[PDB]
Length: 107
Ligand code: HEC
Ligand code: HEC
Ligand code: HEC
Ligand code: HEC
Image 1 (cartoon, protein in one colour):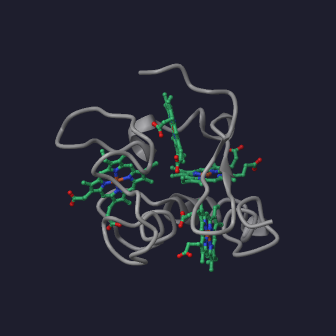
Image 2: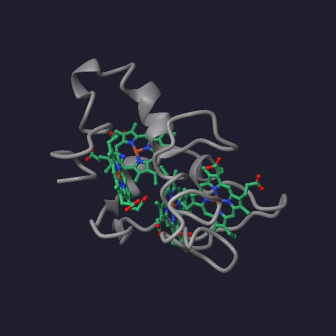
């Protein structure tokens, strides 16, 4: 796989800007985040050709909002998903990882 960027990449969602650091995610299998596509390893931007590059839907596989939060049972493992289990480790962090605001996601 490509060389993991030691720098965080901005994820200009709908309006608010959120940057995700890889360092803090250098112990989590890529797949874990970079799910497979048609059983074909890929690493295209969250919003790559025929992917999640439409925040005008709000709900749908063509949305980068229902695959970012969705802390429910999804095909893969959403962010808020994992973070969910994490909170089960540092109950005193139920926000920094799962915070709508005043967090490391929504400052
Ligand atoms: C990282 C740990 C996040 C936490 C915690 C929360 N959100 Fe978030 N949010 C995140 C990203 C990376 C983005 C960019 C675009 C996307 O949808 O992934 C967002 C964006 C939003 C948006 C804008 C999208 C839209 O539908 O207009 C909203 C409204 C939003 N986030 C709300 C929200 C709430 C209510 C949260 C607490 C449950 C929350 N976010 C947590 C990443 C992260
Ligand atoms: C979630 C905890 C992740 C893990 C684990 C890894 N990466 Fe990642 N990567 C993540 C996000 C949220 C993004 C961009 C978000 C967006 O909306 O664009 C990325 C982006 C990359 C990129 C750039 C293009 C792309 O594939 O999106 C590369 C080259 C990349 N990531 C590499 C990479 C590798 C090699 C990983 C395993 C060692 C890896 N990432 C894990 C989130 C996450
Ligand atoms: C195009 C090559 C894609 C890119 C880039 C990413 N994903 Fe994706 N994802 C893609 C498809 C075609 C589908 C449909 C699922 C199916 O049943 O075939 C998905 C699905 C997801 C899901 C599950 C859907 C849900 O219930 O919300 C999640 C959680 C998801 N994708 C996350 C995700 C993230 C975070 C990405 C960037 C880091 C990402 N995908 C890139 C195709 C593509
Ligand atoms: C488990 C499989 C995870 C998934 C999926 C995602 N993240 Fe995560 N995140 C995880 C851990 C264990 C931690 C703690 C940091 C550590 O030392 O391991 C985090 C932290 C973050 C942070 C804060 C970074 C910090 O300095 O504490 C952010 C902003 C964050 N995570 C964002 C994020 C996004 C946007 C994800 C989906 C694209 C995502 N995480 C997935 C574990 C996991």
